[PDB]
Image 1 (cartoon, rainbow, N blue to C red):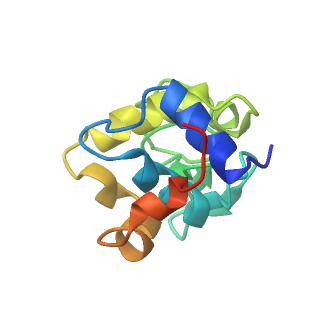
Image 2 (cartoon, rainbow, N blue to C red; image 1 turned 45 degrees about the vertical axis):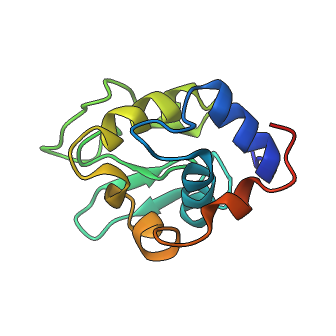
Length: 129
């Protein structure tokens, strides 16, 4: 599923991401935009053999099992394919654990490089929230 901007904002808010660990809703929408272009089916291979999955490009090296990242962890206790569903529950719940990890949203390279220190509120401008 390719979410609309305000559509994903609403879904993320409903799932309790707005101000989760102090990060406003705009930060999450901005991250999702630059990680996946709001596309739940997005996948990208990393140099180390791991893969990033879903709207927030969650990585198999630590967070999910994809059956082809040997010697990795499955900290969210899910198959990586769960992160590709039209239903974003699995992605959001795993993102909550990631952002609690100690590095906050810096865990997302696209957020640090493209969202951090910018007017992230603009990402939820106009939405009926």
